[PDB]
Amino acid sequence: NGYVLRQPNLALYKEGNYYRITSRIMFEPRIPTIADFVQIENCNVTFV
Amino acid sequence: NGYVLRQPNLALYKEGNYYRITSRIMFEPRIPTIADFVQIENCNVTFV
Ligand SMILES: *[C@@H]1O[C@H](CO)[C@@H](O)[C@H](O)[C@H]1NC(C)=O
Ligand SMILES: *[C@@H]1O[C@H](CO)[C@@H](O)[C@H](O)[C@H]1NC(C)=O
Image 1 (spheres, rainbow over the protein chains, first blue to last red):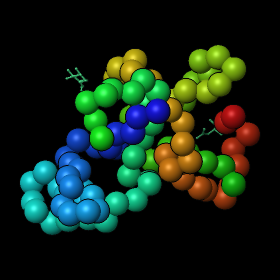
Image 2 (tube, rainbow over the protein chains, first blue to last red):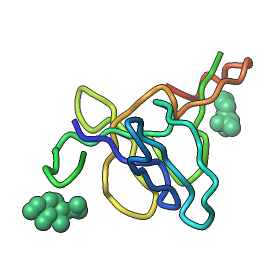
Image 3 (cartoon, protein in one colour):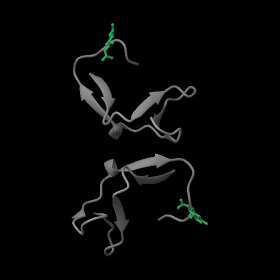
Image 4 (spheres, protein in one colour):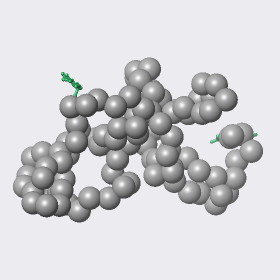
């Protein structure tokens, strides 16, 4: 299983050791959580 | 409690033994999860 985001306007990034997901239009950062993801069986290697 | 979807553009269906929820505008299928539902007390019999 590979996970993706529920809507496009967000984007992950590696801020430091931890990972932070920000908006695409502003630099405001938001905490990661499990509710923000969605499941798809086929894994693409190109992801984290 | 009866559950419904967080936004209208989705739709459940019984693909096989398991249930799959797809987009209303494309046939792309997405995995079921609990985060995609919402609770309402009154149960309508007309649902699954
Ligand atoms: C999936 O990974 C392949 C690896 O070669 C990459 O070329 C492709 O762009 C990726 N597709 C995506 C991320 O949708
Ligand atoms: C609720 O179920 C009743 C069962 O008679 C049905 O007639 C009605 O259309 C349903 N309402 C919904 C699904 O909003």
